[PDB]
Length: 128
Ligand code: BEF
Ligand SMILES: [Cl-]
Ligand SMILES: [Mn+2]
Ligand SMILES: [Mn+2]
Image (cartoon, rainbow, N blue to C red):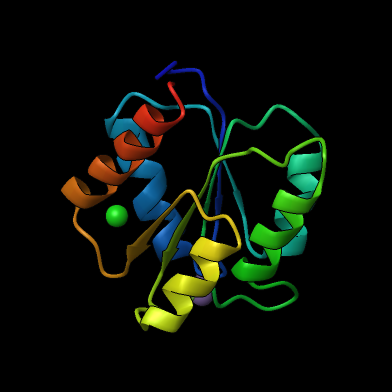
């Protein structure tokens, strides 16, 4: 995929954001911003330029399922790739996110290999 693709990495905790940012760097993606919750995310996203979202689930202000739903419901960004990255591992949570239009779903904790496989699975699916 184009190494200029702009990423938004959303999570209410630094540690996770820093892990993902660094991993993206390792893969050749340096165009990366962070947000701390769904509201913060939608703000940056509305400032334009984003090609990919990676999002936590449990966050104050707006959780990741609500964020995903909002993104899918906005006509300007309804096809933005959204990859969930969360501790929520119950099948009902996976179903709910999938049905809400998640592009992919990784369960924390994850390996570097897992994140790369899943990002690539999404690239291939969307012909990126
Ligand atoms: F807080 Be997340 F959903 F891991
Ligand atoms: Cl999968
Ligand atoms: Mn913190
Ligand atoms: Mn969280």
